[PDB]
Length: 99
Length: 271
Ligand SMILES: *[C@@H]1O[C@H](CO)[C@@H](O)[C@H](O)[C@H]1NC(C)=O
Ligand SMILES: *[C@@H]1O[C@H](CO)[C@@H](O)[C@H](O)[C@H]1NC(C)=O
Ligand SMILES: CCCCCCCCCCCC
Ligand code: NA
Image (tube, rainbow over all chains, first blue to last red):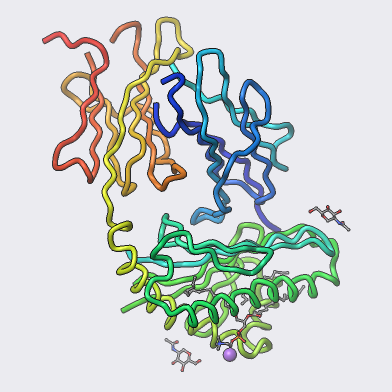
């Protein structure tokens, strides 16, 4: 007798230039339970040394975390956020858009 | 409006594995953290001490440590009977908003279980059998606890929160001007492009990113969630779909900008 919510992945940059150092943010919202696996990707490879939030939950008790790594973007580079959770049948890759 | 509170997460995986984790919050602003393993308060900011003596805070840190461990200890002791009810998660939200009002909300599997009203532990109207059982033991069996919880939310929390606000005076009332830009993105439609208007790295959270088709403000854009940045600032993006070259702009209104609002023009205008 409880709740199961699927994570809401949201990907963005701390600032808008190639070669100029930035921060990639992956914000995972409203999920049940807390057991979550959030990964950050550089051309599909799991980015190591990536800091994150202390787990917190919204008014409605759904959890949330902000994931971040100091990154330097380039033309040929593809950045995305891979999240896997009990509600998810297979991981969810969410691409960071640019242009 | 002034609300300080602690949050606790008690994750109960199996007969043996069960962990606990806390945080110290001043609304959206995190002020404290909890070393789950060691049982040590983490003061995130310079002013996280507030006005409280370290002899105080240590005794507080201590009481928290005992409780963070004991709650798990006592929970796994009851769960030692029905190894089927595994896994499950307990959630705690408790503090005060300053006459001043205190609180203690509890959730099970992300659904209100019980509350602390005056000195009575009151079941959330719904799952009776588990709540009524817990509430009973809290109201009539664990003797110290109720008075302590009462004291923490009504005597300590208001005393602390007042201190913390006078402590973080500059940081809590700081004004961070937004970094705003435009962006193009292929829409799903033939001869249709998306117009992303960004406003990043701003604080306090209340912001107003609006797309204008020349004169009028256009509702019918894709407003995002005001999202967090590691630094403490906020981020917002509003998407406007346009057909193959449609003279429009983006007005950004933030508390920080001195009565002025940022305007961002996409391409050419034709008056
Ligand atoms: C309990 O769950 C943990 C995962 O959190 C697992 O590593 C461990 O093997 C489990 N133990 C038992 C006895 O089920
Ligand atoms: C709160 O409960 C106490 C008994 O513990 C009682 O004396 C007091 O009058 C009650 N007040 C309210 C507002 O219910
Ligand atoms: C095993 C059922 C979950 C028990 C949840 C206990 C929550 C009560 C919090 C108040 C203790 C001070
Ligand atoms: Na009591």
